[PDB]
Structures are given as C-alpha cells and as structure tokens.
Length: 78
Length: 50
Image (cartoon, rainbow over the protein chains, first blue to last red):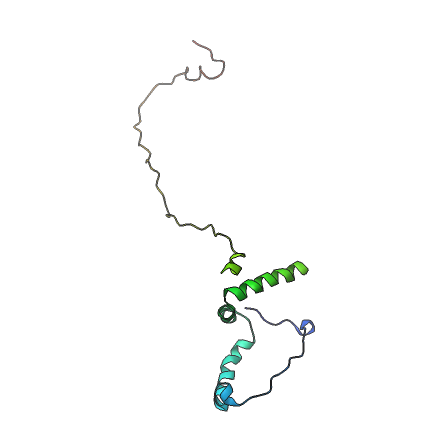
C-alpha cells in the first residue's frame, strides 16, 4: 500500500471543488449520498490493490499503454 | 492491443516435473576380487616394464 508523505514534503495544490447538484444526479437521496460517501471513506487514506483494480478497468489497454509511455517520459526527464 | 503490445516481451516461463529420472538407470555392478596389479599405469606417460 502507498500512503501520504509528511507535512513539509506534502506538495499541495488548490482544487476546484464542484458545486453540489441535486441528490438524484448522484446516489439518489441525501441519506444514500451520506451512506455511500461513508462507504468509500475507507479508500481515501491509501492507494492499493482496489484502486489499481479500478484504474485498470477504467483505463483499459490503451489508457495503461499511454500512462506507462508517459511515466517513462517523466523518468527520462528526471 | 497494438499500443500495449509495444511495451511487451515474451515471458520465458515453462513447466516441467519435480524429478526427472535418467533415460537409463545405473546398472548395479557385482564385486569381483582381483589382485594388486602394478602394471595398470605403464601405458600412462613414460612407463617402465618388469
């Protein structure tokens, strides 16, 4: 598993937090939104096999290829 | 598949048996008494005869 570094090395950058839409456009209701955000709260404190599993599906062969190719370029540059 | 194919190579992994006995098992040799013979090295190097 991967975890976040210590405070002085934590490179923060401002995120444009999205305006909240109506519950029907998310999980369905306020109760369900709260329930599901709690469910997925567990996954925010690390990066591991479940995250990698999801990344794999959502990117497919083409997404993985381009990410690998680009990571190689980051490494070449560094 | 073509795009990911660029980043691939063959994995050289194969399957075999835990133990493979030799094609021919070593033949058991019977013990035969023979006297001390001092001539068995005469043909090795510059030998000398009795």
